[PDB]
Amino acid sequence: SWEVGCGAPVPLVKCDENSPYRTITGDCNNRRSPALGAANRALARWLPAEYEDGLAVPFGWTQRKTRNGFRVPLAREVSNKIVGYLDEEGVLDQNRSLLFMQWGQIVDHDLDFAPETELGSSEHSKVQCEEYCIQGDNCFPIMFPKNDPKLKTQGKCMPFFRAGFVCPTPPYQSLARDQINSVTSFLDASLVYGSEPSLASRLRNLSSPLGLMAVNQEAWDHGLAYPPFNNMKPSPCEFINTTARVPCFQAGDSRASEQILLATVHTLLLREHNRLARELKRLNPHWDGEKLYQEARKILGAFIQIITFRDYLPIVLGSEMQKWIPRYQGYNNSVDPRISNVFTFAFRFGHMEVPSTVSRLDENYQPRGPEAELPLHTLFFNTWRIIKDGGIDPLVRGLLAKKSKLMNQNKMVTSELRNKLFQPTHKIHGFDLAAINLQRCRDHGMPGYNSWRGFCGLSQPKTLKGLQAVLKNKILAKKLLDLYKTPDNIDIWIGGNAEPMVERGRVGPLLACLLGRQFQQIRDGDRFWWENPGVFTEKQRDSLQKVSFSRLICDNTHITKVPLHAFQANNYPHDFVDCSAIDKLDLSPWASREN
Ligand code: HEM
Ligand SMILES: *[C@@H]1O[C@H](CO)[C@@H](O)[C@H](O)[C@H]1NC(C)=O
Ligand SMILES: *[C@@H]1O[C@H](CO)[C@@H](O)[C@H](O)[C@H]1NC(C)=O
Ligand SMILES: [Ca+2]
């Protein structure tokens, strides 16, 4: 009657009340409402979902149905007209390393996932969708516009399948359609350890009772670990080189192998854990397997919290930083720590920070190997270039010494993503992350640009001139009003990202507001925030305050020259210093004083 809850699946909850550890599923973080910010629950709605039929069907589903008296443009057309660009000269960010981009993706992956409906098993309908392009129940294919190069070479559509939703897939969902966040809303390193108990356990070395995360027994990197392989056929990392047959890696997050540098940063994180559990043993030889695991896990979740909040968020938000994320004042139980649906789009700003090439560098930071730099597209689901060529060390140097793409109103998303994206089970390097993002906004029943501007106490343009004034771009504004007719209809993703960057930051005001609230909320609503009184000891927190991405590299690679500030643009050797000048993590406070 009153729709107390829609979650018939995943009822299991036992809250140990005295537990000194987060759960894997993020359940029992909040006490009054223990499901808040836990994996497998619905994404939060900061505003009501806007659907065609006000329930589930996305805007753009039915031809003859309008938003506010206008038809929504095609995703791919918005992509072609606005998002795409030819010229890769000039696009690089003078003050952000490629690591800047990377960490965004890491943090994102920790926070949210809304995977597709997994409905087409023992069912051709996931291919019926693919090659026939027939708009089905959860098949929502992206149609090419009439002047599109991809029409000529690669069919009539790009395939797409709607995201999963609570109260399973087959019947009408109670009330409106809400999408699942399949990972924990907390900045908890879930991408390393998993969000379900199954993965969590399968990821660990339970054979050695020293609380280590299971590593690879088939290949090594100069005596340092790799992630174990996920042997589940088909493997898209196998698919891309059939000769190499190197499968995708296995991590606490499914998407670890989407691209080589994410797999790389996943590899650093795993290593730091092992490195932390091996030490904990020395200082505490009496600790059991799980105590070593659990106690290293909290150090790592804390590490991710510090890098993100101290180093990453200030250079994303800049001026807006303090307006949205005031300095810490302790856990508030009344905060909603759940990731909002809109955040999983706000944080796609990263898509425009991704450049068209990745480099491998040697100890001199020179082109390592003849084919040193490679097109980004050849690196989707590519694990073999880690195993068979060079390890992670040369890649990590690229992340330091190269630049992120700067976002640009005339150059938004590289073709490497716009036209050449690889998606599992779809064979071709031929897709568009931009088009996909736009279709996803609709899929998810997103309110439009102006709804979100209103929500953030910013103005809502109605005219081309209004929009021009907001975007500070006559032409961009013009192209958007030609497509969307009204700014009320501009898809949040393209609308938020169109806004010029606030001072000393990399997003506009709307995104700064959206991101800001979310990252404010996940800090304040988290009972195990590293800096929450009680989580760590005073002695521990002064040891923790010293963590640095610089250090994580030194500890977990053979790289002995790093910058002080890894997110700034840093050039070798001018801004590089030895690993001996950089603060280690002192693990002495973790020694238990027994008798
Ligand atoms: C080469 C780099 C990257 C690739 C290839 C990539 C690719 C993708 C793909 C395929 C999706 C799924 C889209 C969908 O089905 O709706 C996605 C989602 C997403 N990406 Fe990226 N991405 C990259 C970098 C980044 C960066 C740097 C960020 C953030 C700074 C980011 C943030 C996101 C977020 C927040 C989502 C939504 C995740 C969810 O809730 O499901 N990505 N990306
Ligand atoms: C596949 O990998 C082998 C090394 O394993 C390499 O020499 C070859 O270039 C790769 N082929 C393609 C098409 O990626
Ligand atoms: C806790 O959160 C609420 C709403 O989320 C906020 O208005 C209030 O100021 C906070 N209270 C404390 C004790 O900080
Ligand atoms: Ca998480």
Image (tube, grey):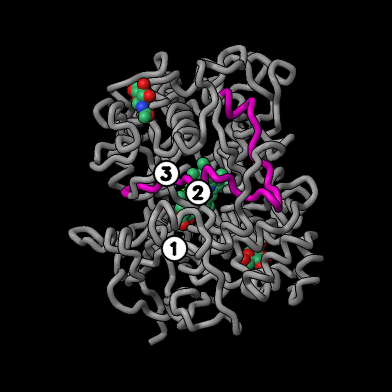
Q: What residue type is labelled 2?
A: Asn
Q: Position of residue 177 (x, y in %)?
A: 42, 74
User: Do the CB atoms of the residues marked 2 and 3 lie less than 8 Å apart?
Assistant: no
What residue is pinned by disc 3? Answer: 429
Q: Which residue is drawn at 44% across and 27% down?
A: 271
- Read off the magenta span: 397-425
Q: Which mark is residue 142?
A: 1
Can residue 14 be seen from the camera position used here? yes
Q: Does the magenta stretch include residue 412?
A: yes
Callout 1: SS: strand
Q: How crowded is mark 3: few (under 14 residues within 10 Å), some or many (20 or more)?
A: some
What residue is pinned by disc 2? Answer: 419
Whether 355 is drawn above or below 36: the answer is above
Q: Position of residue 230 (x, y in %)?
A: 29, 37
Horizontal side, residue 494 vs residue 183: left or right: right
Q: Where is residue 77 in the image (x, y as percent from the top left)?
A: 55, 62
- State which quadrant residue 48 falls in: bottom right
Q: Residue at x 69, y 29 (%)?
A: 565
